[PDB]
Each structure stands twice: as structure tokens, then as C-alpha cells.
Length: 192
Ligand SMILES: O=CN(O)CCOc1cccc(C(=O)c2ccccc2)c1
Ligand code: NI
Image 1 (cartoon, rainbow, N blue to C red):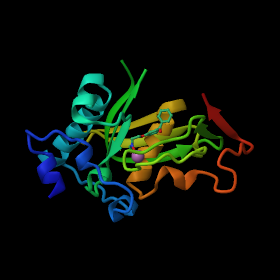
Image 2 (image 1 turned 45 degrees about the vertical axis):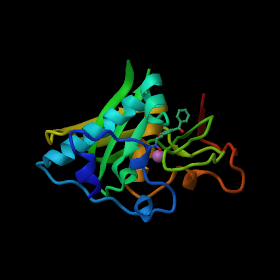
Image 3 (image 1 turned 180 degrees about the vertical axis):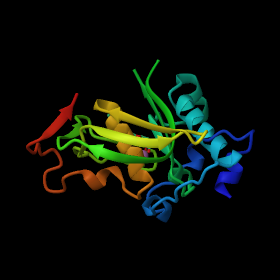
Image 4 (image 1 turned 30 degrees about the vertical axis):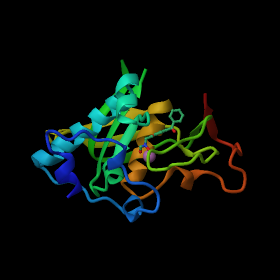
């Protein structure tokens, strides 16, 4: 069991735990977690966040051969559960382990990072503007089953949507304009 070996106290998540394109799991819709959470589900969220911090540490990332990341979703670890971790640097602009996250409202205005996007499960560069909602209101539960409702914009908004896409089986390039990858449509805000 992926969640079983990953949640072992001694286990450190690394690139070898992250599945890549082709693996059906990344295109499957993740199952919601029930409350109360099991100890493994709590530990998993903590392991995921630990990985993000390790991936953002020069020495640590080097040692473990880690790709820098600002977010991670359980499906990427071959665990089909609606659990995601986000860690956006400013200490941190956003630090959160989210259970059953859901977008409950979104702006009509769209947004896209001017540099495009990349994915830990994608070993290649896919240029283009990843079209997302500029702003989103997200509901999620923390490890204690406490509900949170937050509003995100700018970079944080993009990052959370990218991870939520993973628990719904969507990849970043699925939102890039096939015709013109760098086309600027009315209402699209380019971030940079
Ligand atoms: O699912 C998780 N991953 O694949 C890890 C990466 O997650 C994310 C989430 C949102 C954006 C990106 C980027 O590619 C990026 C673009 C410009 C500036 C900074 C970041 C990566
Ligand atoms: Ni990704």
C-alpha cells in the first residue's frame, strides 16, 4: 500500500514516490476522505508538506535529488484521496494541508502565469498559458475536521487550482490553448 509505506515514521517522500504521466491514477477522480481522519491520513498530509519544505531547501533538495515544488496532491503519490499540500514562498505566502478542498466561488476574470506551469509528474516542458480562474474561494478541512473558507488571488490562486486539478484528474496542459498556446483572450490576466 502506497499510503502504508509512505506514512511509516522513517519514510521520507522523494521523487521515487511520485508517479508520472501514463499512470492511470493521475487521470482518476480522487475519493473524498471521511472524518474523523485516520492517523495515516494525517501523517500523509504532514509527509507531503515535509516534502515541499525539503524540495525548497537547497541542500536538502540536492541531497534527495528533489525537484522544487510549491504544491503536491496525494494522487501524485498514487494515493487516490482528496488531500493536497501547498507551500508558496513570499516566510510563506501560503502554507496549508487541505482535506477535501473545493472551489465554491470563482471570478469571471481568468489568470495565467506569464512563465507557464510545470508538474512533478511531468518530465518535460510544455509551453503555453495555463488558463485558470483569477480568484477563487476555497473550502477545505484541516486535520481536526475544522472547516476553513479562504479567498485566494495571484500566485496562491494558481497553485491551489493546480493541486485541486490533480484530485479531479486534470493536468495543467489540459488548460493551455491548443491553437495558440500564448493567446491572450479578453478577460485573461497574465501574471508576472
Ligand atoms: O502538483 C504539484 N506539482 O506538480 C508541483 C508544482 O505545482 C505548481 C502549481 C502551480 C504553478 C506551478 C508552476 O509551474 C510555477 C510557474 C511559475 C512560477 C512558479 C511556479 C507549479
Ligand atoms: Ni502538478
